[PDB]
Amino acid sequence: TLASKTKGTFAHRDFSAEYEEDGKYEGLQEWEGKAHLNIKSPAFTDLHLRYQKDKKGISTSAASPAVGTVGMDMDEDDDFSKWNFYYSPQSSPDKKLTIFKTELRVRESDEETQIKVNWEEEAASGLLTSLKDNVPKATGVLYDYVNKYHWEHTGLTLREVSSKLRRNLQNNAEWVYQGAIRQIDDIDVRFQ
Amino acid sequence: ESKRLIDLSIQNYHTFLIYITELLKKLQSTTVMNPYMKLAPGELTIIL
């Protein structure tokens, strides 16, 4: 039997990663334990994923302030199998919009088997809206992040880089223009 | 443009889903053999 306990922590200037896992292992696939990872980005939205595996349930949920909480729970039993995939919106963390649900049921009488698959349109459309609203959020945070690094390295923005490139190109073009004019004057003079 | 595309996609998805649910029910309202099924607007159950 193996008893595994690991902790990995990374520290830098725009986040910190802290992953703690504990568990036990027997047989060939008899693993049981928990695993919690926490990323804390000052530059971005943080995230915390929790994985749990016990002999009568596998529950994994990731919580991020930007998206919400995406979880999936699997319960296996000799008479029923239940798979649930849910996305709790950040606006209403109390509710768990079941993205999809699967029920496998065996019948102790006769020879029948029930499969029940359920999907929610409301959950799907809500997640779509959450993603389309996080797109501008991601764009803004990434733009501010790259501007912050530009200030860190040079101390400057991006639009000023555009203006600097324009002015330098204009200076070079005017140098070429005056060179052409003086060359025409020189060749005319020497021809005369 | 991304949000416009996503709006059109949500619109088309929600307009398609009722049509396909109707089509599924019409197809399943054809015959009654030993296996049985149940359809709901967001659910499908099958019995062996």
Image (cartoon, coloured by chain):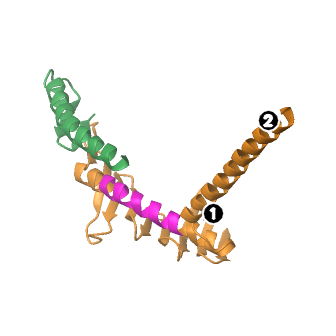
Chain colours: A orange, B green
Residue at the spot of label 1:
A26
Which residue does the image show at 17% across and 37% down from the upper left?
A: B18
Name the residue: 62% across, 58% down.
A167
Question: On what subunit does the disc labeled 2 rest?
Answer: A
Q: Please name the amino acid that badge 2 sits on.
A: Asp
Q: Of A124 and A51, which appears nearest the observer?
A: A124
Task: Identify which residue, A186 or A64, lies in the foreground.
Answer: A186
Residue at figure coordinates x 60%, y 55% from the top left: A166
Question: Element at badge 1?
Answer: strand
Relative image position of residue B39 (x, y in whole percent): 18, 37
Residue under pointer 2: A188
**A99, above or below A184, in the image:** below
Mark 2: give few (<14), some (14-19) or many (20+) Cα within 10 Å.
few
Is residue A43 visible to us here? Answer: yes
Q: Judge if badges 2 and 1 mark residues of a common chain.
A: yes
User: In the image, is A103 to the left or to the right of B22?
Assistant: right
The kind of residue tagged 1 is Glu
Q: Quadrant of the N terminus of chain A?
A: bottom right
User: What is the residue that sits farthest to the front in this orientation?
Assistant: A192
Q: CA distance from mark 2 to mark 1?
A: 94 Å
Specify whether residue A27 is in view. no
| Residue A77 drawn in magenta | no
Q: Residue at x 82, y 41 (%)?
A: A186
Determine the main secondary structure of the stretch shown in magenta: helix
Q: Chain of mark 1?
A: A
Q: Which residues are magenta?
A: A128-144
* Chain-order first, disc 2 or disc 1: 1
Quarter of the image holding residue A32? bottom right
Of residue A120 and residue A3, the one placed in the foreground of this image is A120
- For this orientation, the residue located farthest to the right is A190
